Amino acid sequence: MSLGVLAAAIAVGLGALGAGIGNGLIVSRTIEGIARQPELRPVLQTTMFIGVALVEALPIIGVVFSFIYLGR
Image (cartoon, rainbow, N blue to C red; front, side, top):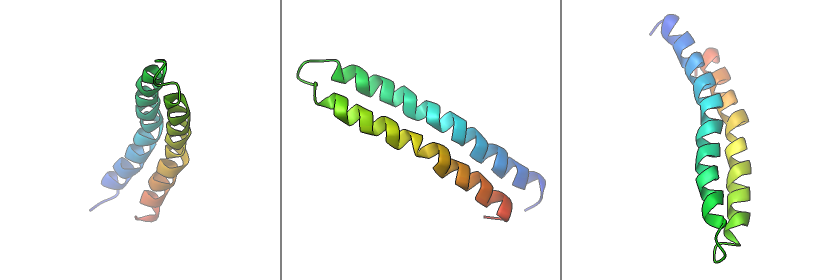
């Protein structure tokens, strides 16, 4: 309950924003790797959608951080 913590809420949203994309890219990396298989040929499509969905975390989280400032 202060201003300092507030900034922490922002620095957090910004951290999970850029970090999030990385967490989604990391998972997407391994996800797409499994698709590399023959029986997992269709998995590629699943990895492609999972990647984009992960990109939706950039703006999503970005909104969170912004919301924090507003005071949540």
